[PDB]
Amino acid sequence: TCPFYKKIPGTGFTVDAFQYGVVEGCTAYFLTHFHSDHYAGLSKHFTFPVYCSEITGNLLKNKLHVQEQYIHPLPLDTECIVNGVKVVLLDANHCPGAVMILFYLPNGTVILHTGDFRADPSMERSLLADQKVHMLYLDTTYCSPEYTFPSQQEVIRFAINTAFEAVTLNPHALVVCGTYSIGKEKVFLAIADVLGSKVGMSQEKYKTLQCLNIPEINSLITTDMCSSLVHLLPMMQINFKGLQSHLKKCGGKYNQILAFRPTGWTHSNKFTRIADVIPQTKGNISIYGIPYSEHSSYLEMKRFVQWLKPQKIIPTVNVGTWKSRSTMEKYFREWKLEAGY
Ligand code: NI
């Protein structure tokens, strides 16, 4: 059964609630983004209205084969009416097509559901500037001060400089980038741009990328692996055994691999600055873990919430343990006492 933090009170709406069968009283199912923990349960047999971004709707139709009659794509930054209730979708700064949802309830209550997000000061000049928010449904993934990591811009500078140096020293090197979901496309696109190459990948991953409305994408990606020196592979294959195996398949075109594993936060972020990061190496194979996050750091999250000044916060991540719930509630109260709301 559907938990309480996935239901929007005063409405017939749920958010990211497809794995519970038919939810009693739900007339519209919202999907914030195309990540499997959130879409879990959707398929071609789903027969209620799904509300989402255009990009999420392209993925639902082409990857999960949801029928078109049940997909309701909404434009961003635009007031829409769904089952008699005013809604707005806002860019979440997460993966492609990810949104936050503003609900203006009939009784005057205003609710913001962040979905998954990476808070940014640019959100302080969205359509949120105007107004009061009574309830915030918050992505609390990294809600503790130990969670630090660099800007996306610093991490991409490190990746492009590392890949450009390696291939300039060795023109016969191959670069590989792991993936297991949408998001983090800047990593492989920026590296291919500095090397003057298209990105090579499987037909399945190409299909996914073709649903994302990325400008000039046809100029940037390919299924012809042999024509490319930046390859995408499943994240599970980014290890010395899977990379050795891949190099065999390339028919003596390359004599070295440089590989990247974009992660979220890891333990080494407690100690090692991005500029100082080194790879794991075995023979002619090197593997870099790089902390490219699509969720808020602790500081980014705290800034956003102290700006917004919501009356009540409902966490949507780390809700399963009493220790996590207590820790999050203590930080919410600190933030409220410090800022005076
Ligand atoms: Ni996500």
Image: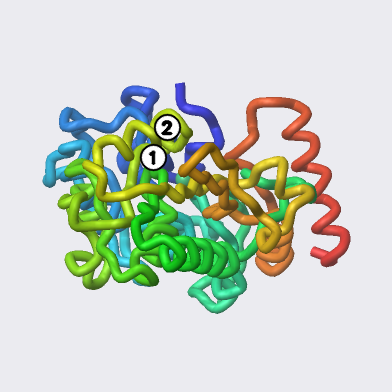
- For the residue pair 251 and 128, the one nearer the viewer reads as 251
Quarter containing the N terminus: top left
Does residue 275 appear left or right of residue 41 in this picture? right
Residue visible at 36% across and 37% down in the picture: 234
- For the residue pair 222 and 207, the one nearer the viewer reads as 222
Q: Identify the residue position indicated by label 2 in the image.
A: 236
Residue 46 visible here: yes
Q: Secondary structure at mark 1?
A: loop
Residue visible at 50% across and 75% down in the picture: 126
Task: Name the front one of labels 2 and 1.
Answer: 2
Q: Position of residue 55 (x, y in %)?
A: 27, 57
Q: How many marks do you count on the picture? A: 2
Residue visible at 55% across and 48% down in the picture: 288
Q: Position of residue 29 (x, y in %)?
A: 34, 41
Q: Is 156 above or below relative to 209?
A: below
Q: Amino acid at mark 1?
A: Tyr
Q: Secondary structure at mark 2?
A: helix
Q: Amino acid at mark 2?
A: Met
